[PDB]
Amino acid sequence: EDLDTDNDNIPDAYEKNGYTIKDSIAVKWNDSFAEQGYKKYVSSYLESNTAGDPYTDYQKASGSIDKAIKLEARDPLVAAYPVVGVGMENLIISTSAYINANVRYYNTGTAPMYKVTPTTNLVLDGETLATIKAQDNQIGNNLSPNETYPKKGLSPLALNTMDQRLIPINYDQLKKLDSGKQIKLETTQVSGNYGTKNSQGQIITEGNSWSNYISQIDSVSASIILDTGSQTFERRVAAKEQGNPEDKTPEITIGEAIKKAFSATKNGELLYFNGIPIDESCVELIFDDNTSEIIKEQLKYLDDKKIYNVKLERGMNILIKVPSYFTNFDEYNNFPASWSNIDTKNQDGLQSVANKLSGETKIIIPMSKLKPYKRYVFSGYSKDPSTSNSITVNIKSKEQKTDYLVPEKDYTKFSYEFETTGKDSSDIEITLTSSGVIFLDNLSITELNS
Amino acid sequence: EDLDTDNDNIPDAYEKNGYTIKDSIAVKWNDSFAEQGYKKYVSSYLESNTAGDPYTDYQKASGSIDKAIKLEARDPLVAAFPVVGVGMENLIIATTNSKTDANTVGVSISAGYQNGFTGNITTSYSHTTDNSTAVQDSNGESWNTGLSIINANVRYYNTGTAPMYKVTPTTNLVLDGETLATIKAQDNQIGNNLSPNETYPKKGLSPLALNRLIPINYDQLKKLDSGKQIKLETTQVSGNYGTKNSQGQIITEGNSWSNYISQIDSVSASIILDTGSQTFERRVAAKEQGNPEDKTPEITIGEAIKKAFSATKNGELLYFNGIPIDESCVELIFDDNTSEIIKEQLKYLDDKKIYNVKLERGMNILIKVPSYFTNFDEYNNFPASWSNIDTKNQDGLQSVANKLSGETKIIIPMSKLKPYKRYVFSGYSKDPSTSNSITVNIKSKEQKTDYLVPEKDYTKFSYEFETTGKDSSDIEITLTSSGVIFLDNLSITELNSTPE
Amino acid sequence: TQVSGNYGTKNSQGQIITEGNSWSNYISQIDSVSASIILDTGSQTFERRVAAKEQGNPEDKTPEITIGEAIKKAFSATKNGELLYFNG
Amino acid sequence: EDLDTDNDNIPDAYEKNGYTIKDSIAVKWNDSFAEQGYKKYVSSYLESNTAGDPYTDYQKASGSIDKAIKLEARDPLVAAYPVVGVGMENLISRATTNSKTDANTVGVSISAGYQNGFTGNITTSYSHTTDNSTAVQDSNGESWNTGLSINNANVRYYNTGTAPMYKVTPTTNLVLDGETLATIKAQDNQIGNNLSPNETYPKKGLSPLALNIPINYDQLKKLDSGKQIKLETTQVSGNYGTKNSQGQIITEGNSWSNYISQIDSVSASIILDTGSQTFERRVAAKEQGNPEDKTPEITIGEAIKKAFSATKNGELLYFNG
Ligand SMILES: [Ca+2]
Ligand SMILES: [Ca+2]
Ligand SMILES: [Ca+2]
Ligand SMILES: [Ca+2]
Ligand SMILES: [Ca+2]
Ligand SMILES: [Ca+2]
Ligand SMILES: [Ca+2]
Ligand SMILES: [Ca+2]
């Protein structure tokens, strides 16, 4: 009962049903360990590195790795994949001419990246001027998770050397630069190292590279992203191959994976990221085209009919954006202007109460606290047992929108995309009309890409 | 009891309840060893390197490491961390620098303090890595005179705990909001030796020259003429440490420091102590919040300061080489997230003292010792002697207080204080009746006065007064009391500098 | 002022290696345990070094020899009883 | 009586009371070994290297180390330490001589009477032997400005330590008595292959080593009025000799920068000047706080005689007569 096929210092039976690390020796999981704060881990018994990252399944679970890797990446299923991107602050051209920049390396993965050597392009409209690689002057020694180089409170670093100064080929670039065209900065690849403890016990990060592992880590994991409006966290969760009978990676629900990748606690049934709810009813999801067809196909054959109860797959991409303005009519309403014709004396809501609307809903949102030239999408829950009332929308924007909606028997989410342009433009108006008595809950406002 | 889960030549039983090293082996700690000078160590029995530094628990306790590492790094909880920075001392188209200017500048101090939290609040905490320049060349004239419309002399200074061989900084010189350039020391300004609390070149040697043409905008020079707020920021430094090998000869070639930086900052609480002359930086280990497998010991902030700086406890006061750094005698500058952590834990306490709260991960504590202080008991380094003080009292917070009924005067020459530096007034008052009134008046560049009322218990007050110039009127402090009022720990603290 | 070169040591594999070797390591050591002797023949010059014991050293066992014997040793000059001839 | 805690081939009992090396083994010291020229050695029984220098207690006591090291460093308490520098010779068109104690005794206050017991002085600008200040001898009275009236360096590296330095690459700056000019480094052809104790590169009898900068008109006046130029040293990077199992002395990779902050922090500097040649010795000592520390505690008089190898005839110290 102690066979170890893959030789990762964890028995096959424990690795299949769930195991927890106590006294640095893995033992069978017991439900009585929940109150002490122990976590449950389940992984594959046919492979040493479940997610593909350098660290094994006994090193990740026990925490016997680099201590800068976030405590969420101690879960074997979640790859310790670091994401690094370069962000521009100031771009100036001076005499063709010399070009300088002010950039800071943003890390949002889960593990540090020593000796960062980013590679960037200088493109303005399709045409790329040159490829820039970080020389000795701009290599960041340490880049901890969720931290920048230079760290917060230090000025950005310059960038003026391109090969063994920056210079265009001719004046054809500057003539269209003055016409109103600017130069963007985009990253193509970032190079780095990963820390490991050598034979004698010290850490060495010379012969180890992260770029020997990226191709593998991407291909065996499902990408998940969470955006808080200001901070982005990119996580990768291992997923099993479909037709392979010898691929024994555990299958988990998408709802389960969110709790694991972002280490978000669960207060019984709701999920809080760090005080921000991330339950499916109070947050907007974005999927690519490939995910949409798969997620719809799985839902129709399952009775509950919620996203957060669908088994994860290998290669699906998920983008989660928290609402900018959200009200639940129970404990939170961040809208600067109060809503009209609201009645909280109800018990038919999704969680506690619903809004019994008698007539129409009128809300005037100021543009002062909103982003100009940005695309906004509103969402909400509508329930009508009568199924005999027609509801239309009249919202002022760059182009006035007028759409009709027929509420269903039960609660249903409606999403309508509109665009707002110009800071010194007409104030945005929103109108909701109901034929009879309707139930509304969980209204959302979320920014989209421009 | 010789079980070894981590295999670091320290049994689990010793490593939990207290162990000391005798004859290069670890033995059970006994309370009778205290007077002989042996120290009590407690560590984690599941980790080889409790503090995260490259030297394990047994190596740190026994001292079998580089002999330049300070004796207060031999505690397994304290960590070796060379906190190197670059300070500039020459402007080329004279300079006195401070390592705690950007950290004590962000604090705004009110008249009173909330009951329980006898500390200050700042939202701009910064380490001693950075530099702040207040050029002494200015005497009323700006730099624009004479010349109007590249290479500077700098000195690498270490304030950490362990030496850094092969110094190779990477600093940025600010140009208002914009920058100058990313300058990386390349071949012939690489200090091969940087001893802790020592510079490169040596203390008595002139600074070396930074390397070959740069542009400087003239519009920001007028800003410099408006105020010399130019500060030098060191983004990163590269170097090595030294661990003996099988043969014995110290190797420093592959052993970079930069491998254990993102690990030390992620397992340790940042604590800084300033004495006015030089500043020390330490990073004590702290356990994780919700990890049951984290066996890092729990020690309160009072023990953290004693361990980090090897402070000695006389009576109930921590003494740091003559200068007392007890909680009631020093001005603390916490970070906001650090401060609110203490605030919530204070109301669950009984004694209600800062130094008795438990240490946590991620704290940022900047201890700033006041320039002039007197406890009325034994220490009084004031440039003059205060008038109308009755030392013979028994209601003092530590030993004695003063029986004040009337007015108190003090003479303070401008010479004995640094010009153009903001200062914060501090002290403790108490009155059993709480019916008398306290009136104060501050003689400075502006005429400022205020009124105060005591309470049953000792209360802390804080007042601000700035200094201007070298030739100016002497600063006078007047304390007037209606009835009987008791005073203790009368202090003057040196805060950030004032704009030109 | 100085010269840098190599010397050869027959290793375990039977070859002669002059890559991990240098004379600079031994110039200071040879100079400190030996007595300099020069022979000048008008057109050619010779320079040797003969080891000798330290003055006040109890654990030094370098043999004691005379100047005449050392010149005989350092140049391999034959001695026909008492007269000493180098190359005639 | 055979226990060895530090494992340096010296039994702990012999190491704390006195020992000496006969036939490459340690023997208990006795009073009868004095007249035979033997010395008495005492070191710390918890540390392989008491002084901090690369050579252990057994290698120094038995002499199984470099033969170009002074006998002074064979005592376990005395650290082998190559304190070197740069000696200015030519100012370019005028030569100079260099004083190793000018910059130290300049800050000494001298009075008439003295307090009881104490018979020394006080210095406010203490500096080491690497801190070299010159004194121009060819300046007969004419100013340096004379000759042009319009508004290189020949040097010689010097050693005053106890152990030879191979691959000497000194680093200095042109401080020009008030402000540095250039942090010059000697890279490829100015490197000294070997630098023996109490010897210079080049050796005696060879032309000065040349090393290859603007000078303002203001420095010309001040240099012409009671001021002198000095070339302080910030650091010098060298190597040292280590034996092998194959028997070769390997001096590549081994550095005199790894042990410098170890030797320096555990040793008490003692300096002696005879007026013509200067010496610097480091002597190991013990910190008061640590009880586990076992470095022996001896007087200055014992430290003087064990550092400069004087002779104790009667009760007075004789150094080279
Ligand atoms: Ca297994
Ligand atoms: Ca496995
Ligand atoms: Ca509800
Ligand atoms: Ca242990
Ligand atoms: Ca341990
Ligand atoms: Ca008192
Ligand atoms: Ca021994
Ligand atoms: Ca020893």
Image (cartoon, coloured by chain):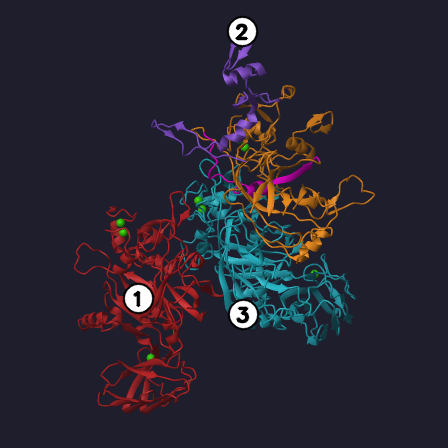
Chain colours: A red, B cyan, C purple, D orange
**Front-most of residues D85 and B110:** D85
Hey, what amino acid is under mark 2?
Gly
Q: Secondary structure at mark 3?
A: loop
Label placed on residue B217: 3
Tell me: A43 left or right of B199: left
**Pair 3/1: label in front:** 3
For label 1, the residue is A224
- Residue at image mark 2: C81
Where's residue B138, x and y in %? Answer: 66, 67
Is residue B353 in view from this perspective?
no
Contact between marks 3 and 2 (CB within 8 A): the answer is no
Classed neighbour count for the residue bearing mark 2: other residues with Cα under 10 Å, few (<14), some (14–19), many (≥20): few
Residue A447 appears in view: yes
Q: How many marks?
A: 3
Determine if the C-beta at disc 1 is less than 8 A from ligand 2: no
Whether residue A448 sits left or right of residue A100 in the image: it is: left
Residue B36 lies in what quarter of the image? top right
Q: Chain of mark 2?
A: C
* D159 vs A252, nearest the viewer: D159
- Give the Cα distance between marks 1 and 2: 101 Å
Name which residue type carries label 3.
Asn
Is ligand 6 closer than 8 angstroms to the Cβ of mark 3?
A: no
